[PDB]
Amino acid sequence: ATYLIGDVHGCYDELIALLHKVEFTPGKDTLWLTGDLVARGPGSLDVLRYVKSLGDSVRLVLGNHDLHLLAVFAGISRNKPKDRLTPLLEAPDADELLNWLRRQPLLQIDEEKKLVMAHAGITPQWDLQTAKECARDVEAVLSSDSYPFFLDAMYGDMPNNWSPELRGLGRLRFITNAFTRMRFCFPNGQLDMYSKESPEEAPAPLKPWFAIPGPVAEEYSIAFGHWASLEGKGTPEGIYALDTGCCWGGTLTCLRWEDKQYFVQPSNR
Ligand SMILES: [Mn+2]
Ligand SMILES: [Mn+2]
Image 1 (cartoon, helix red, strand yellow):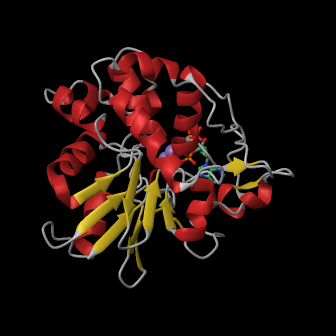
Image 2 (cartoon, helix red, strand yellow):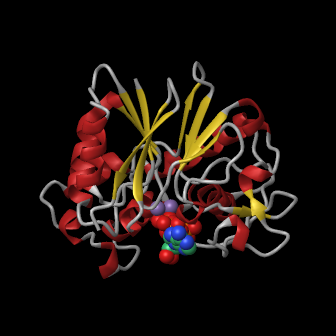
């Protein structure tokens, strides 16, 4: 069976309870995770240990909080107490866990399932070939010995419009923002980096990225997490918003792909 789970955010107890609910069995089953494995919940260290141990039985994409953790680890960014990352950062296996984490993809594709996953989704300005190339470029910098330089460069809100002519810092910043921070788009597909509200609360002319026709969404199902204020609701056919806000007192959601059956684990908070 194939299971897809939204942002875990250190909610290790809820993750394990949900996996036991579906009798997740590595070697027979595969788990897809939308990223944001860490921060806010209390168990980021246990989450990363478990997810790394799954090996080929997990398909992860990196989220904005995973990248922020890497930036803190590398001395690029300041540790915020509310993220509760200190046990992970001080763990004796922190190097092993975080060097594993920075080698994971920004994008997962299963052609037999016609299924694509990224943390925030797929901008309508990208076709599949471009999404693949952009994921490869950022994965290459994150997996290199020089990844702290990229982590420092990644912060920023511009450029917010894709072009194949983008180069250098702006190209990487756009790619990172599209995969890990996107929510709303302008009608032409350009990213808005400020509004984090539900679609009903957003100001015109902002619309969700998935409300703008794009070539990937037209051919593939897209699963994503990230946008907690969506509460997993309000998406069109073939768009699966899996982040139902477990770390916020909401729920952890798991979708089984074969029958599109949902399973939900209440937050312990
Ligand atoms: Mn999140
Ligand atoms: Mn996120």
